[PDB]
Every structure is written in C-alpha cells, then in structure tokens.
Length: 22
Image (cartoon, rainbow, N blue to C red; front, side, top):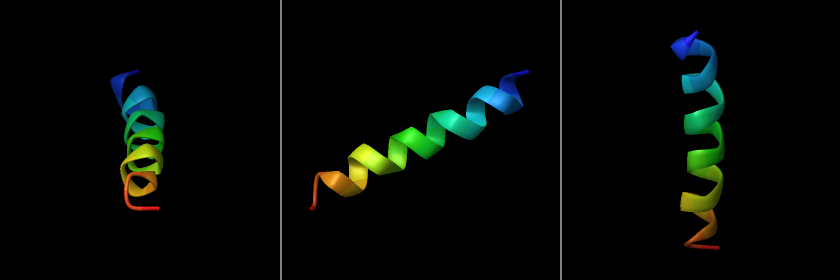
C-alpha cells in the first residue's frame, strides 16, 4: 500500500537530508 511505501520514502528521505548537514 501507499503506507508501506510512505514508510521507506520518508526513511530514506531523512537519511540523505540529514547527510546534507553531515
């Protein structure tokens, strides 16, 4: 479902976003 995808989507999203500052 979208919820399953939403799960990984934001997961990987934050990883690179936080990596911008690291």
